Every structure is written in C-alpha cells, then in structure tokens.
Amino acid sequence: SVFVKNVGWATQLTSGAVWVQFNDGSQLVVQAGVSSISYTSPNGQTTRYGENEKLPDYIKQKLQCLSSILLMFSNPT
Amino acid sequence: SVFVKNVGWATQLTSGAVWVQFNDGSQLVVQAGVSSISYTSPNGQTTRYGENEKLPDYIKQKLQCLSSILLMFSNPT
C-alpha cells in the first residue's frame, strides 16, 4: 500500500533523527534519544551505562564512529 | 585508530537497538527510544507527537515501514 521513497538521518552523540519521505508525498521525522549504552570489552567483561551517566573518553571516541549522516533517494528512469 | 567492523540493528515501532563490533574486538550496543514524531501530510499540514503519545492507525502503519533488521559483516579476502 504505502512504501518508502527517500530516507536520510543525522545521528549525534547522545541522540539522533531520521527523516523519511513516502511515495504518496507524506513525510515522517522521528526523533530518538539514547536510553542505555552497553559495552562489552574485547576480553569479555560487560558494562552498562544509563541515560544520565557520564561517559569515559575512550568510550566517547568509540561512540563517535556511530555519528553519521545518510541520504538515499529513489531514482527512477 | 579504531574503526567499525560489523554492525546490526533491530528497530521496533517506538524504539530500536543497534549492535556494533569494532576491529579491536570491542562491542557497542545502543538502546534508543523515540522522543518525538513529526508528520507532514502530502498537502503540508504538520503534526507533532510526543515521546509517550499514542499513535493513530495511519501513523502506525507508516511507522511499520521503518521497522527493519540489518546485519553487516566485513569480509576480507
């Protein structure tokens, strides 16, 4: 019935937003925020962080790799 | 210094989770929840929804198109 035509997002450090445009012309803008962060070390100890907890520097630099901006367009003919 | 090797996510209607694995073996699991939803109709009237607010059926069916599960692997040699 209804499907996606164009998408795009911009994710910051502690939140993100997704923009979507459908075939019928409607648009959906979804704002999302981080509720919890889980980090398992390479040797196997797990550590969960909360919505308000402070993040260490070596965790922040790894979270920076997730921050990105995407754009995709349906390009017929 | 540190970059991403494998990613994956599973998005529900009002939230989502992203799984990421780095080259050094570390893993990041990010839980996110929707804070606000903006819907502009094809003719142009906007409507904003809240973090907890209920959604009409024609909004839920369009949000269902966003729900997806992705998985990506780095495949050297």
Image (spheres, coloured by chain):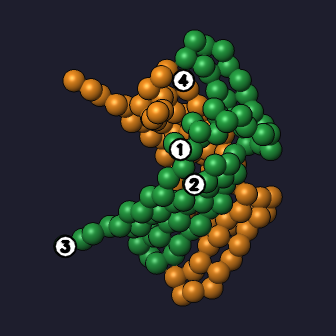
Chain colours: A orange, B green
- State the separation of the CA atoms marked 2 and 3: 31 Å
Query: Residue under circle 3?
Result: B77
> Is residue A77 or residue A29 the one in the foreground?
A77
Neighbour tally class for label 2: few under 14, some 14-19, many 20 plus, Cα within 10 Å: some
- State the separation of the CA atoms marked 2 and 1: 8 Å
Helix, strand or loop at mark 3: loop
> Subunit of mark 1?
B
Give the x, y percent position of residue B40. Answer: 62, 21
Task: From the viewer's perspective, tell me whether residue A10 is left or right of residue B59.
Answer: left
Neighbour tally class for label 4: few under 14, some 14-19, many 20 plus, Cα within 10 Å: some
In terms of sequence position, does the residue under pointer 2 or pointer 3 come before the other? 2
- State the separation of the CA atoms marked 1 and 4: 14 Å
- State the separation of the CA atoms marked 2 and 4: 21 Å
Check the image and report above or below for B77 versus B67: below
Helix, strand or loop at mark 1: loop
Query: Residue under circle 4?
Result: A26
In the picture as drawn, the residue positioned furthest to the top comes out as: B43
